Image (tube, rainbow, N blue to C red):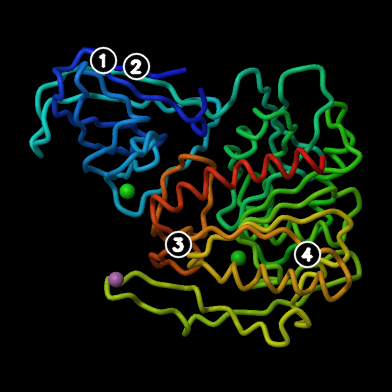
């Protein structure tokens, strides 16, 4: 009676299989993991073995559980924390998560007898990818190099509000042949402890660090940002030299809460108003409307002058984003480019998808503490639809950077 995992990194699909069951036996499968602070994540699903007493998750549908239907990776993407408002993250990329898998007898709520167990390590630092902390000038970052002679096409990776240095996107990208820089800009070592001003000179220095590194191919670098990071990536593309291609995931394309400055140019903030928060029946807060109206549309003074960018731009949007109206913004950015005689950016819009489009099989966190506001907010997204968005967006990003870098 045995559990098989064929043929490995968190974002890679795997085939889960069970041999040695009774013919057409009713079983529950359960998956579990403790994250880096000891918080528990779990998921389960009910199945029936076939006539040979075999179960194959790529062919047999879940009849119920944390999800239902033909979902081979569901036991991983549907994982939910015990503790509410707790988000699935990876802070130490060099240590894997261990997933405990278990096959239990029956479909009963009170779990049946243990038929088998298996522990599989899921990785965030792919095979032979080398990691190095970067302290160069004021730049605080981490560099990931693929294995091989090199040099490699280079990408800089920028998160939104939250601060610190999260590496997990850059480490996984490094597994596809890109040198990648995870870049911190506040709330990390000696960097400022806040976000009162975005000064682009800091990010220019990170570009310069990358383009001068012996293992970074060039002539330009790729930029990948989410949220405020996406906006910073669009600003960098608009103002700096040697940016070859830019991907924005749920960016806004405007200076929002804080001015964007570079040398003798400043983009004024549009501002927000907290009276525009909406409290759901549940008590959750929805901030999607707090920002001031983008009057004039693409002519609005708060617009990042993205017509200045020399390279191509890809905009990725969660249609169910509750942090802000990423879909509306992406169109306006498109309208801005077209009006100054540039090519339409590529826009990919994902239905049922929220603000936080993570790498593949990262479980959705529907709501958590918003750090500025000190209240629990919804982020948007439905688990199944969000999960397919995260799988597809990864491939779109790889294809885009492959082509342009
Ligand atoms: Cl489902
Ligand atoms: Cl922000
Ligand atoms: Ni409600």
CA gap between label 2 and label 3 equals: 35 Å
In x, y percent, where is residue 322?
Answer: 48, 67
Q: Residue at x 39, y 72 (%)?
A: 285
Task: For the residues labelled 3 and 4, say whether their Cβ atoms are less than 8 Å apart.
Answer: no
Q: Are marks 2 and 1 in contact (CB under 8 Å)?
A: yes
Q: Are marks 2 and 3 in contact (CB under 8 Å)?
A: no
Using the image, determine if residue 82 lies above or below residue 18. Answer: below
Question: In terms of image quadrants, where is residue 23?
Answer: top left
Closer mark to the observer between disc 2 and disc 1: 1
Q: Which residue is mark 2?
A: 4
Characterize the local packing of mark 4: few (<14), some (14-19) or many (20 or more) Cα atoms within 10 angstroms: some
| Mark 3 vs mark 4: in front | 4
Q: Which mark is residue 344?
A: 4
The picture places residue 246, in percent across and down from the top left corner, at 76, 52
Q: Quadrant of the N terminus?
A: top left
- Please name the residue that numbered disc 3 is placed on: 379
The mark that comes first in sequence, 2 or 1, is: 2
Quarter of the image where one finds residue 300? bottom right
Q: Secondary structure at mark 4?
A: loop
Q: Secondary structure at mark 2?
A: strand
Note whether ligand 1 is within 8 Å of mark 1.
Answer: no
| Whether residue 50 is situated above or below residue 231 in the rendered picture | above
Circle 3: is it few (<14), some (14-19), or many (20+) Cα within 10 Å? many
| Circle 1 residue | 19
Looking at the image, residue 237 lies above or below residue 143: below
Instruction: State the mark number for residue 362.
Output: none
């Amino acid at each position: 009676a045995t559990l098989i995992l064929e043929p490995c990194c968190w974002n890679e699909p795997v085939r889960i299989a069970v041999r040695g069951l009774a013919p057409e036996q009713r079983v529950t499968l359960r998956a579990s993991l403790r994250d880096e602070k000891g918080a528990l994540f779990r998921a389960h699903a009910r199945y029936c073995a076939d006539a040979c007493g075999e179960l194959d998750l790529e062919r047999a549908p879940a009849l119920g559980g944390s999800f239902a239907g033909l979902e081979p990776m569901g036991l991983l993407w549907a994982l939910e924390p015990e503790k509410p408002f707790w988000r699935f993250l990876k802070r130490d990329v060099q240590i894997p998560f261990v997933v405990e898998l278990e096959v239990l007898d029956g479909h009963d709520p009170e779990p049946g007898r243990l038929l088998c167990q298996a522990q599989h390590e899921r990785h965030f630092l792919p095979p032979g990818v080398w990691r190095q902390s970067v302290r160069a000038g004021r730049v605080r970052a981490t560099l990931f190099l693929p294995p091989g002679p090199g040099p490699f096409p280079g990408i800089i990776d920028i998160f939104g509000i939250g601060g610190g240095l999260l590496e997990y996107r850059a480490s996984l990208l490094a597994g596809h042949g890109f040198a990648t820089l995870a870049l911190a800009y506040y709330n990390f070592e000696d960097l400022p402890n806040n976000m009162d001003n975005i000064s682009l000179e800091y990010f220019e220095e990170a570009v310069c660090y990358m383009l001068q590194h012996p293992q970074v191919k060039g002539p330009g670098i790729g930029l990948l940002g989410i949220s405020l990071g996406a906006d910073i990536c669009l600003s960098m593309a608009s103002f700096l030299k040697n940016v070859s291609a830019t991907v924005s995931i749920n960016g806004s394309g405007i200076s929002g809460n804080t001015a964007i400055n570079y040398k003798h140019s400043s983009i004024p903030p549009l501002g927000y108003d907290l009276r525009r928060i909406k409290v759901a029946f549940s008590g959750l807060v929805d901030i999607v409307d707090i920002r001031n109206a983008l009057v004039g549309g693409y002519k609005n003074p708060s617009m990042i002058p993205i017509e200045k960018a020399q390279g191509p731009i890809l905009l990725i949007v969660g249609q169910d984003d509750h942090n802000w109206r990423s879909e509306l913004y992406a169109q306006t950015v498109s309208e801005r480019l077209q009006a100054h005689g540039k090519e339409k950016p590529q826009i990919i819009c994902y239905p049922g998808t929220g603000h936080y489009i993570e790498p593949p099989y990262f479980p959705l966190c529907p709501a958590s503490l918003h750090r500025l506001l000190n209240k629990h907010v919804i982020w948007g997204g439905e688990p199944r639809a969000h999960s397919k968005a995260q799988e597809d967006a990864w491939k779109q990003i790889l294809a885009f950077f492959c082509k342009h870098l």
